[PDB]
Image (cartoon, coloured by chain):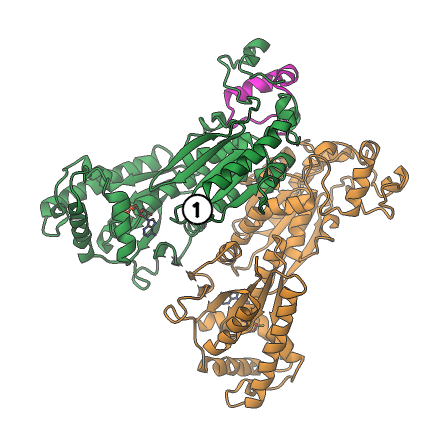
Chain colours: A orange, B green
């Protein structure tokens, strides 16, 4: 109903920006327009580089900048939620003083925005050390210049902040809605979840982690309907599909993965591919391939022939459009939520799925736009190794040397309802 | 993998048995075989009625009973999870002493069961007073005998327990996995969620409440395919369907409901029915009617005719069996989880859905067996008013005086693959 401001709270190197990023994507992915407002960003668009002195309490000159940055950011927050139609604005900054939060609660009150706080609390020198190593050594601020000096300036930077740090108080802040995250998710305290969005966020946040691992995404081996250029259905693996299943298992074994979890759909082709691994795996009805409704099992030609208007309209909006009695990519994404969440909770996991399902998952992990999503390239017999990294995720494409047919169909240059068959089928790949 | 024991912790009249009940059902509903072990039950199968003195600390005689009851219960817990294949055994008792819990953690350790604690903490005389009013005045113990004396004996009963009460300690119990619920869900503290089942439980528990409200379940008004005796599809409302939509709105208005929330599917018939109310409502793709795959839009006759083996096998296991390219009731239930949860978070809500969807929802709220579920009677143009009550839920069937066709098809006496058409269609209701 009314927009929301999610307020990050915590000392530097507590993973606020990491949590800001992840949550923002998650929410956006499930249909909630969210944007992050990072103060550190604003700051750099202001003064500049050198010292932790800029963070010194006596530095009144510095405090104005930071104060003007906070208000600039709020300006943006307002027009984002009030004029641009955003749903959630995440305020990413230390916000360590009751004072600062009040400023915020105030602004919120004025504009009628609900407020939820996320406080990341961690007092393990180890954890913080790694955080600085991991993300601060290469922060823009520290144009990779110094050595251990970066640490020096940062530990100091933190200290500045430790001075007036006023954590959310269970008594004084009793009325506020928030979640305190302790020791990278070991313990949590949740107070006053007001609504859906908040019940949701708490859920997401209490289910993500920072344990290094890899996510391998791939489709089932080439299927009989694949070879025939027909979409959907529940065909089994082709000979080539069966060969890939074992090339995959060979690859997986070569990766020397610690306790790998395997997920499949309830569809035969993914299950059969899983069997090749000789390890237990789990089936998820939610990973089944998108459903084409009336075009289930057709060839693009038969679709152009029987449902030409649908065909062109779908090409006009592949993300939202549905074939009669079928799902849209938007639909699939919604249905995939539970899986995405399970993927967050897992460490090393291999997911054997389908072309459309896989596009959704990649779009999620690689932050592609919904516009982009229905068109990602998910070739058969190719493994995509996803390695999450602080704010981000690298990806490696690994072809497993077993030929298969090509199922990627690019957007035709002509998507008009009155376009002609050839114009509508000119991007269809060769199928047997 | 290994079973789990969920341990209820808390003073009497904190809603432990209420939480035990709800969670057990929830879990069972989502595919996790859970059973409750209520000690109060065991006790009554032992000594008997009269005093709070049975709960007096000096009462060593009483303590043995209670001690033998706890071990009896544990015996059962073991054979339930170790021989009967249960997945979660919920230990419902005060378990207010570190001692008692150790006994439990011990037993657990011995048998290799994971352990999670749920501590209900509430220090509002008001809240507790109502609880005693609400559930204790009519407890078996207090064969509705006394008046305010019941209270007397109960407040005293609680006191006995207050003496040695040792809440979970954030330091001493740091290693344990648990969730502390404060003031009927206002604040929560979660420590060390180990796995899926636990991440799940926390979610459920942090999303249910005890605010009195009603849940109205009904189908869309009679549809065109309804009138034709055809299943599935996305037909619109019949004239009668359109008349019911407004009889419904009339009824809803007559109930004088405070802020009623309305949910529909993405299917036309439920949406059209919603329109009649003149209030905003929300569409949920997950409420769409079960999908019949290849029998989508057929009449039972056409199904018997084209897929006779499927037809009989489905009659053999209507819950698990799937029509080619279609869902099973089991499937539907899984897909409905998100909705059930949203229903828990809502207060007054009206759900306009479909025959199979509605059976699932009723089965959930009325605790019917999966065997029973696919056969519940969900007549058209009839509203089912569900009123949750402490451990339970009453239900009222309200016919809205607009005729519609009958779509209930009972299980045939003959479900053999070799049974004959007439034998397979003899329970089909009249359709136009
Ligand atoms: N709850 C957590 N506690 C501690 N570290 C975490 C947590 N969650 C994520 N991290 C780590 O935090 C690091 C990233 O830290 P940042 O997000 O830069 O912290 P931040 O300094 O609070 O963000 P800025 O200052 O707004 S850029 C990565 O190493 C993450 O693994
Ligand atoms: N977190 C909560 N705190 C306080 N009361 C609650 C809570 N959740 C449910 N209730 C109420 O608790 C009452 C039922 O109490 P019980 O479950 O009998 O408590 P209990 O006495 O802990 O259970 P026994 O003694 O094992 S039968 C109903 O009024 C519920 O509304």
Is residue B93 among what the camera can see?
no
Foreground: B74 or A387? B74
Image position, residue A186 (x, y; %): 43, 61
- Residue that label 1 marks: B197
Image quadrant in which you'd find residue B41: top left
B317 drawn magenta? yes
Image quadrant in which you'd find residue B122: bottom left
Residue ID at (36%, 55%): B181
The residue marked by circle 1 belongs to what chain?
B
Residue ID at (60%, 30%): B241
Foreground: A208 or B344? B344
Span highlighted in magenta in the image: B299-326
Image position, residue B260 (x, y; %): 50, 46
Quadrant containing the N terminus of chain B is top left
Image position, residue A132 (x, y; %): 55, 74
From the viewer's perspective, is residue B260 above or below residue A9?
Answer: above
Foreground: A153 or B214? B214
Left or right: B308 with respect to B64?
Answer: right
Question: How busy is the neighbourhood of tag 1: few (under 14 within 10 Å), some, or many (20 plus)?
Answer: some
Image position, residue B326 (x, y; %): 61, 29
Left or right: B146 with respect to B387?
Answer: left
Q: Is mark 1 within 8 Å of ligand 2?
A: no
Q: How many marks?
A: 1
Is residue A53 among what the camera can see?
yes
Quadrant containing the C terminus of chain B is top right
Is disc 1 placed on a helix, strand or loop? helix
A219 drawn magenta? no
Image quadrant in which you'd find residue B289: top right
């Amino acid at each position: 109903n009314s927009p929301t401001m999610v307020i990050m709270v915590g000392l530097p190197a507590r993973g606020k920006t990491y949590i800001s990023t992840k949550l923002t994507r998650y929410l956006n992915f499930i249909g909630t327009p969210t944007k992050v407002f990072n103060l550190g960003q604003y700051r750099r668009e202001a003064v500049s580089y050198k010292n932790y002195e800029f963070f010194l309490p006596d530095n009144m000159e510095a405090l104005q900048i930071r104060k003007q940055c906070a208000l600039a950011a709020l300006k943006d927050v307002h027009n984002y939620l009030s004029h641009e139609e955003g749903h959630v604005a995440v305020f990413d900054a230390t916000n360590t003083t009751r004072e600062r939060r009040s400023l915020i609660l105030q602004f919120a009150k004025e504009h009628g925005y609900k407020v939820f706080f996320i406080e990341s609390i961690c007092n393990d020198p180890g954890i913080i050390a790694e955080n600085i190593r991991q993300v601060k050594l290469g922060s823009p601020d520290y144009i990779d210049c110094d050595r251990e000096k970066v640490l020096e300036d940062f530990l100091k930077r933190i200290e500045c902040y430790e001075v007036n740090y006023q954590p959310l108080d269970e008594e004084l802040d009793s009325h506020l809605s928030y979640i305190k995250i302790f020791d990278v998710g070991t313990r949590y305290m949740v107070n006053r979840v007001q609504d859906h969005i908040q019940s949701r966020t708490v859920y997401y946040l209490m289910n993500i982690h920072v344990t290094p691992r890899s996510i391998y995404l791939c489709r089932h081996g080439e299927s009989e309907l694949n070879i025939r250029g027909r979409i959907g259905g529940d065909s089994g693996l082709s000979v080539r599909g069966k060969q890939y299943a074992y090339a995959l298992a060979n690859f997986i074994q070569s990766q020397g993965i610690s306790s790998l979890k395997v997920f499949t759909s309830r569809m035969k082709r993914t299950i059969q591919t899983a069997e090749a691994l000789g390890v237990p795996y789990e089936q998820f009805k939610a990973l089944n391939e998108i459903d084409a409704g009336v075009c289930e099992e057709m060839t693009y030609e038969e679709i152009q022939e029987h449902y030409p208007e649908e065909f062109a309209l779908r090409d006009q909006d592949k993300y939202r459009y549905r074939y009669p009695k079928g799902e849209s990519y938007e639909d699939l994404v919604q249905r995939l939520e539970p899986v995405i969440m399970e993927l967050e909770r897992q460490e090393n996991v291999l997911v054997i799925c389908h072309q459309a399902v896989m596009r959704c998952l990649l779009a999620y992990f690689l932050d592609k736009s919904s516009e982009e999503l229905p068109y990602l390239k998910c070739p058969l017999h190719t493994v995509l190794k996803l390695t999450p990294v602080a704010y981000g995720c690298k990806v490696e494409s690994i072809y497993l040397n077993v030929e298969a047919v090509n199922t990627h169909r690019e957007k035709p240059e002509n998507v008009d309802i009155t376009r002609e068959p050839e114009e509508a089928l000119d991007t269809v790949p060769a199928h047997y």
